Image 1 (tube, rainbow, N blue to C red):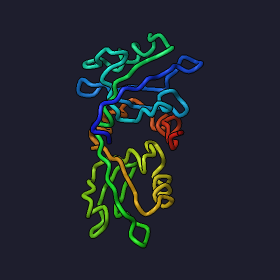
Image 2 (cartoon, helix red, strand yellow):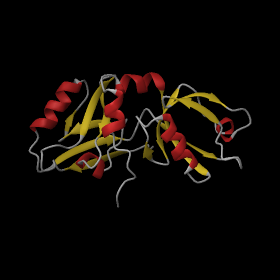
Image 3 (cartoon, rainbow, N blue to C red):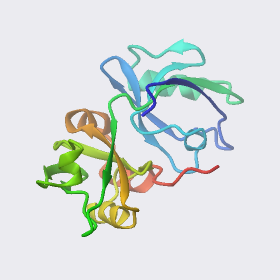
Image 4 (cartoon, one colour):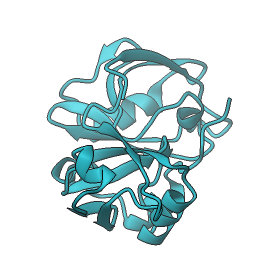
Length: 191
């Protein structure tokens, strides 16, 4: 998580899409969805990113509707955004034991217990936090089984990016749990 504000320059694709859904939260605007293979994923926009400006206009107090309408009207050629990096999230670095374990139990992407004497205990992993990313890979909407899969196939150093569940439940409200699985960019980024 950059303790960092950055500018991103976007280009609408052939269909005039950028591949973003935005959500009003506490009078900011946050990324609810980044569509795979969109302009938004190529410039590296992430779930939970705050959008401060669109074309140098402040987003403060905009409805989810108004932010979508503003995006729909922009001169497609070039859209500037000012982004604050995943402000509701933190990253935690853990090491698997020889039995392959970091030392927690999750359900529907939510950490529900921390296993005593584990790397997760030693690093202060919290319960009631949704898993947003693993080693910088978005995993939101993946079945629990494919999250554990990605953990097994991870090396011994595991980075997890988490969000308080109240905040997570507030952002994804009114996106069907199938569009989360279906269309949320779960790809490793391109270079």
